[PDB]
Amino acid sequence: DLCFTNVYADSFVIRGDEVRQIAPGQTGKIADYNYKLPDDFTGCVIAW
Amino acid sequence: EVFNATRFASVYAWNRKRISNCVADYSVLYNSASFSTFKCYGVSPTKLN
Image 1: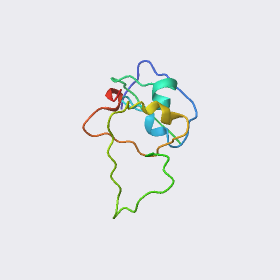
Image 2 (image 1 turned 180 degrees about the horizontal axis):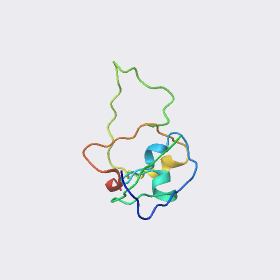
Image 3 (image 1 turned 90 degrees about the vertical axis):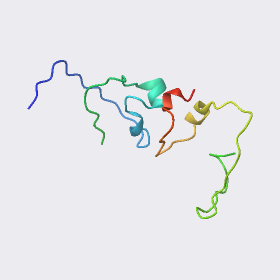
């Protein structure tokens, strides 16, 4: 029921154990040195 | 000594080890240690450093 303003899709591949690190306030190898989400992140994280 | 231990204890006889006088630089675990679960309760993870 919504319209989205500035839609960006960020795609990558990680380990199964590192999927938990894709979150606004996570630490770890991926969250620190590879890909960090903002604290006020608005959007959806999808992993398969 | 903790995450690379050869043998772990049983859950009913879980082992407790004191940690003192050391620098908690957990980034050294990035190379070899992969964790399925990492949940902190009384502190945000990004503040641990």
